[PDB]
Amino acid sequence: SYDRAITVFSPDGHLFQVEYAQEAVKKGSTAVGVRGRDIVVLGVEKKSVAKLQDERTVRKICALDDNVCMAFAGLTADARIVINRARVECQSHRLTVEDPVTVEYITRYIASLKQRYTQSNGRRPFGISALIVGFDFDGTPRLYQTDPSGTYHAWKANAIGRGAKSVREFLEKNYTDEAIETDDLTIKLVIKALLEVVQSGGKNIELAVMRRDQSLKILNPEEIEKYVAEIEKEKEE
Amino acid sequence: VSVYAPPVGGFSFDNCRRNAVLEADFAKRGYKLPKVRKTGTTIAGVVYKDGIVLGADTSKIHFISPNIYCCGAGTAADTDMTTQLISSNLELHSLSTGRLPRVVTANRMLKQMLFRYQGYIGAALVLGGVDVTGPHLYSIYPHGSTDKLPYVTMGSGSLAAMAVFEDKFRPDMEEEEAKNLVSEAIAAGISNIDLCVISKNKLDFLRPYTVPN
Amino acid sequence: RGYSFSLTTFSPSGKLVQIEYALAAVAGGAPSVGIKAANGVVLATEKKQKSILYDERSVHKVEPITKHIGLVYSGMGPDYRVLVHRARKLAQQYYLVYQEPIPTAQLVQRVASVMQEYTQSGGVRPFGVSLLICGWNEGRPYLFQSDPSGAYFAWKATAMGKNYVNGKTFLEKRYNEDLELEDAIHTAILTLKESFEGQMTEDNIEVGICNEAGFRRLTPTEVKDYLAAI
Amino acid sequence: RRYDSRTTIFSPEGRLYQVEYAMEAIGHAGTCLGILANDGVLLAAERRNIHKLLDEVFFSEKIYKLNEDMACSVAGITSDANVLTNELRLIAQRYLLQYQEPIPCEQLVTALCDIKQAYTQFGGKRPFGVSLLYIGWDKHYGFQLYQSDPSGNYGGWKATCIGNNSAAAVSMLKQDYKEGEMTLKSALALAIKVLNKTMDVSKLSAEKVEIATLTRENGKTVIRVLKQKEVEQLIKKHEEEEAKAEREK
Amino acid sequence: YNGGAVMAMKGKNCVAIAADRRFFQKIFPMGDRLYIGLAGLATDVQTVAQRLKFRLNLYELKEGRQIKPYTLMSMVANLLYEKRFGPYYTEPVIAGLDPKTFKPFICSLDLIGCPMVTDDFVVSGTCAEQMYGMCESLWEPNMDPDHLFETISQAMLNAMGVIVHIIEKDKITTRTLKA
Amino acid sequence: EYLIGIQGPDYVLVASDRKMFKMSEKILLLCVGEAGDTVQFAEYIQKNVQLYKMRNGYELSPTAAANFTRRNLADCLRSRTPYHVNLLLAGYDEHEGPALYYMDYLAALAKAPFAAHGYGAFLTLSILDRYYTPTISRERAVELLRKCLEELQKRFILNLPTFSVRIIDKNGIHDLDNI
Amino acid sequence: PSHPLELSEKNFQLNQDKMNFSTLRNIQGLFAPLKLQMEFKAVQQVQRLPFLSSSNLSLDVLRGNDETIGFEDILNDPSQSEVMGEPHLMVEYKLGLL
């Protein structure tokens, strides 16, 4: 018991409803983020590609501002509200202070918004988790993660959704200072991490790339196929 | 308030400051602005033996209920809106009750609604009707004051018509004599003359109420 | 059974049971019929106060809304009274705003919108009434029905209340499109007589009609004359 | 079950049973169909209010016009559908007043889906049991077709179906839909075939089906509802073509 | 600041509405055979024209029928009477044909919305008294569309070009004129 | 403090006093007025345009941007009564093309082929009307601008800046020499 | 402020309620305004979410405004509002979280 209300403590100090809200996250598509030397890369698995579906309306990578982008895993309808709120808050803070917003600032805002909904029995938490990545004003790449409970952390490489255990196990041993030397190497590392849990070739991969003083760019299927072919050739060699 | 608060209906006070600046600015630059339509012609009323006679010159005699009529002077829009609102309220009251309304109810409604707005709605009214109690005549002012009198006059030729009444008014007259007196008093102030006659013999207070056409 | 007490709870098969129970409450009221003729509409119902100790001109079940709109109900009277008052206020507001009498369809839509709200919030109860509304607009008659859930339909002839399936069966085979008002009144009274459970008199039924001249409630003398005629 | 009493409780495996039940409630309604072509969009529905004593007023019973460029069709609870359509019209008029330009279709759909999602998160409220299909045209993407769910989810399709026998209709459309080479006539023929195979009636009749079409003519969008004569002609053509195909065997 | 001048005249199964031009919009269409003209402050004219279309579109969507000129007059009067204590500086003029009967209709309103329905002609602006005599002198009943156009053009010219809309059952004619 | 703008078949030419602001990749907002009020307005408009672009994935058109600015200025005038802002707006469309919009201090929006602000008006507008043609080229437009400035300077006036000019076309905003 | 009638028109129901409560307390006692306030709160605690328009039927019956039409009912229709905020923000504002 002790799990039928949001604000009831277990006899050993557990809030079980907030923990159940993470089982929804653990059932979404895999998302991987890697922080490079002068580049940041995101990647999301594509699941159940219907024949009569439009792919433009089911994208899981969004641009919060000119230098911040995000990927999510969990309930699809809950992410839209958070994305819109963050988009509005970025411009509000730009009005308040002239300088562009900070990745840590927007992550803290998102975390506080998520935490606000775990305080009363009249509302339910957000069943999503996010990977916020971007560049700072000075030019230092950053990467963050947010939990449904309202906690955030800073990472060098991470994964969410199903298969996160295996993807993180792969990344812990394949993430060195040599694999992040170049943008091509970082993209290859992200694709290799995705390919561990994704079958049916590289046709179920969505990639996003952001560089310094540039905007978010989404790679083409032809470019993804070229990278996959290069990786396969190198592995065969 | 705030953009996060739900909206509410009623009057709006958004253009007050801009208009306050603009009117003075145009005055001290020499330009004209649109105004409001006003009426100030003579209106009168007399209580005869078994009814009410209302007169106005040229219609300015409004409809309140099958047994109550009104006349107005001042801003036309204010009189129209007040008359329509009071008529709708009295129709709802009659539908709920099942009997013809009373003159005192209309007088009280008009008094309270005119007093609520502190005289900013300019409408002077002459009210008359016939009840189960009998014929009654009132006079209401824009600030919310009322007088119950046997004869009243409003408009431009008020003095001449009031003199005609004070010279030639007697209680318990006839229909033709009252009509002639009202017509003579109206003509003493100046078009044509419009007369409205409410009679007790043409009203039945025993049958159930029905919505008029 | 666990989903039979709450109003805001869906059944595992996707059903709302309290609305069904409100409809069941409607189905246990007094019978009422309505027939749309070629030049008018007639509404009939069976009285509740079947006693000599009842003052005739005290409470009525057939009420007017505007000069050209009237309605009858089947269910709970206290719930009917407040809906009648709200409908009258809405019609007056429409006339004040647009300087024109309200059409029947707009009034039905507004009343149904009011009724729908009480089926989606906790701590309240749905209305236990169903309404029949008649009107005359643009030289043609109208007839509508409204459920406790906030849904409305347009009918040519219908019955509701106690024993309404057999009434609808009777109406199906006794109805003609190019029908006058008097024969429509005869058919309505016969349909009401089908399941009266007693002996009809001009003092335990109510009849109202709507035509070019407007809505009007019939007097007991005319009802007695019609009953003698049939 | 102890986790399906309200919308504000999670199951141990992370599910929302009240939302699932609301989505299950849609399967009791009638069939609605939508097809996207090269020069127009289509909407076909099934009439459920069939009775000898029912009257015929308004222009349609399941197809509504939202603005000069969009139209929708609902399946579920009519009382909730009315509120949703009124809100859609209000949102479109508000955008038009704000920007002096018509609202895009995806923006309208997202605006309604936010409202639909807000009712599954705050306690004491019952989610809407309605699904919708949207068709329209805008200067950014041209002809479009969308779908919505009681949970607040939407997506863009080329051909889809909601309501009774939705899975069978979707399977048939997927099997026999061509991408990039469809016209309005072929779309109408496919819709007639799918409706005939979907509705559990031995012989299809024109009094239990309604079809609407959207197209562009001389810089204007035209929305019209087909007539019974045209529906009868289409049904007769389909029947004679089926007889020909059977005979040539 | 000059304001403007709007005029409307009634003929035989046709109406005409005219406004002056110098060498902002003052006449807006509200239907197939329905037009409204406004004179006064430009900001208030634009605000009223944009707020009227919102209500008109919502009404036509919900009702399912074309609006009548009398109902448009009532809606304009309601919208003007709200904000009675701080008003818009506009003087509307309405002219159009009945969508189902094809009968002429002209009207005029004031600052706060007191209607005036006239059988022959209406005049709005800051020169109403100057143009009233000309309108009374040059108007005669049962005028063909060409005669109506000529007389309304003369009335506008005898008191800087003008624009005239002629509304017929099956066509609308727009002509820009200079003295 | 003076503004001037000329629209061409496929380009828009503007020139300010050394005051321009950038809202989009193909939209400029030239505003003139009391300092401290003309910067907050531009910042608010720019942030709102950027938010719209972020939320929708495509950019606002000049027409919608001008209507948004007009509505915001009208809402701002009603609260702060000592508020006085004059502004222009220029843009380019993939569908329509060039667009120049004129706005006064009372929030009245008008689309004009050419416009001007500041102390130098009336005669400059008359010269532009006399010498303007719809098919004017960039070099000819620059020639008319230079001759208008020369004609205005001789009337006991001094031009402190060099009147930097810009061009908006299908490629984007281009910076030209200070002429 | 801008007009003498703005503040008076904004706060009318509150002043009327205060006057009725004071008269009732002076005439009958402390219990009647208490009961009236509790009934008002109970019937007002149930309604639609703030971004949609409600009807307020029971509250109107309790207050007595079910047979009266004022200027708040025919001017500036709140149901057809020209501006509206985001649903979640409105709901959070009603709860006092903002």
Image (cartoon, rainbow, N blue to C red):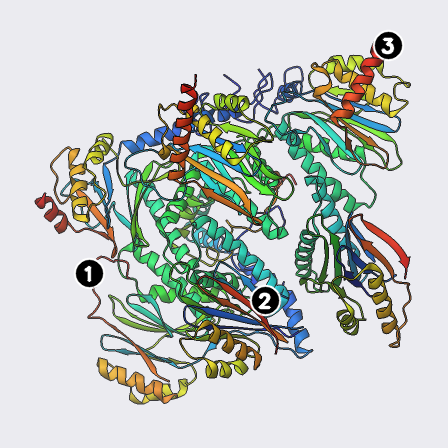
Q: What label does residue A237 carry, if any? A: 3
Residue at mark 1: B206
- Amino acid type at image mark 2: Lys
Say whether marks 3 and 1 touch (CB < 8 Å). Answer: no
Answer above or below: position of D10 versus E118: above
**In this orientation, does residue E77 appear?**
yes
Answer above or below: position of B65 versus G54: below
Mark 2, other Cα within 10 Å: few <14 / some 14–19 / many ≥20: many
Question: The numbered mark 1 sits on a residue in which chain?
Answer: B
**In this orientation, does residue D151 appear?**
no
Q: Tell me residue A15's x, y (percent).
A: 65, 20
Residue at mark 2: E26
- Amino acid type at image mark 3: Glu
Q: Residue furthest front?
A: D248
Secondary-structure class at tag 1: loop
Q: Tell me residue C208's x, y (percent).
A: 22, 48
Q: Quadrant of the C terminus of chain G?
A: top right
- Amino acid type at image mark 1: Leu
Q: Are marks 2 and 1 on the same chain?
A: no
Which residue is depicted at the point 30% across and 50% down? C135
